Each structure stands twice: as structure tokens, then as C-alpha cells.
Length: 43
Image (cartoon, rainbow, N blue to C red):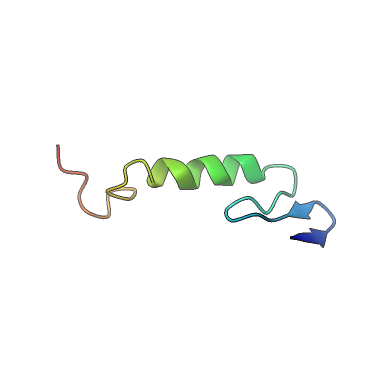
């Protein structure tokens, strides 16, 4: 979904010029997978 200006959204990726940054940060929380420390990331 292209919204205008620089925004070309997929799922975490609403582009601007930096939607790869917020997308990567989002998936790094999702690779705690315990979720940014949501489950305490117990190891």
C-alpha cells in the first residue's frame, strides 16, 4: 500500500525513506521472539 509522499507500507515497512530501519528494529524485537524482553528473554 502506497499512501503518498514516501510511504509504501507492507507490514512494518511504511517507507518515508527509512522503513527498512523501523522494520529491522521491529523484527529484532521479534528475534528476542520472547519479544523485546516481553517474556523476560530468559536464558
